[PDB]
Amino acid sequence: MNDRESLIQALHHTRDRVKDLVCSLREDQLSVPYHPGVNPPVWEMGHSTFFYEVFVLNWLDGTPSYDPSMDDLWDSFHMDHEDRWSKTLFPSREDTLAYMDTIIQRMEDRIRNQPLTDEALYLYRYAIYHQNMHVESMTWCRQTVGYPAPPFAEPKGLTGVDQDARGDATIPAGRYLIGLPANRDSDAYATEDFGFDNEKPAFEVDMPEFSISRTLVTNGEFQKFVEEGGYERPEFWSQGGRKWLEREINLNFGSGEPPLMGRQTHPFHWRKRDGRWYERVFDQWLPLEPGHPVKQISYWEAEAFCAWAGRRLPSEYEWEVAALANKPGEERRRYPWGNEMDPAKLDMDQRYMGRVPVTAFPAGESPFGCRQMLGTVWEWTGNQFMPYDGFSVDMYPFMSTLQFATHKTTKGGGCAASSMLIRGTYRQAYHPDRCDVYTGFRTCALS
Ligand SMILES: [Fe+3]
Ligand code: NA
Image (cartoon, rainbow, N blue to C red; front, side):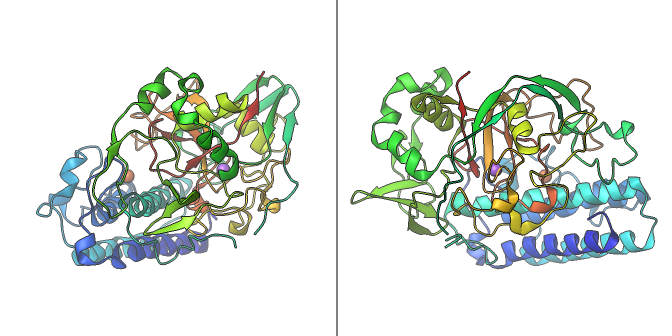
């Protein structure tokens, strides 16, 4: 993108996603059950609109907030999670929609009527992408609480078989390139070198040879681990995993049914019915297909499956090498397949929702033959989410700084995220306990 036409089309597409997410709910659904992983949908709309005012309109022009009384209430750093559920502190769906439409129009007016400097373009992209982060969170909120799929989604997926594009790819030892230049080091920091602070600054790594699966772990592969007692056999689980395994949760959360407190013995959204596995897909239970990727599993579940399988997770640097194969002084790519985004090459944009065969999208393949490095699921890596040496915070300095060390790095972009913000250098931190985000994994051979 980067051109005004692409920018403005992205702005309207994002606005329409947000509006479809809040407007297709009944009024009584706007107040969602509390869960530490969701937010109320009117609040996410107002918060993601406010970001534009803070970091584009007021930032560049000194423009006052549309409603200055809201500045601390729409702020995600100042507003405690639980307080976002107030029916009194926040406007109505109708008024928040009107607020959004006004700000989206100011955005388009400003894009058209002011110079497209690197500084402005950088902030336009950042704010639009931040709103798309909330398009993803709003989509998974529905899954967490058992609401219907969004009207734009096609959650039954690619109906679409599995093929002999499997096996490991071997990445030869060598010196590879990770990340993107620091903003101050690149005149293309608004365009070709755009990324978030955690992608920067770029560095070289001496990589030992390794072998990585060409395909995501499938339901059918994971099902064997589950059915042979994997969750009851703590030899496969790490110290953290065993603690997670012992936690007591409401296993019925999001199902429509009363609370059922218990320990987890299989992926949270799976349910065996008369010996056949099912998965909750928003407000429906669908049969679990063997060749679709296993998804919405914690880091610990992925980690224990690897131990059982005689495999390991990739580090995030092995992951990015296998996805993009960039070397210093050679031509760089941002996607496994090259540098031009085509949404048909990957499962993103809140469409198939991860129900695709793990060998699908051959045009999205990496230079080593790995399929669906981008899209389908965010992939767990072995690393704690940490700043690269030389890190500098973005103008919005909380993009990364609250999630270091406690979270894992995940890579690639999940099915509910938007393709317009994704890159192979992208890093999405997730707490390792979470079962509520669109996470999956592929494995590597032991060293
Ligand atoms: Fe936010
Ligand atoms: Na992926």
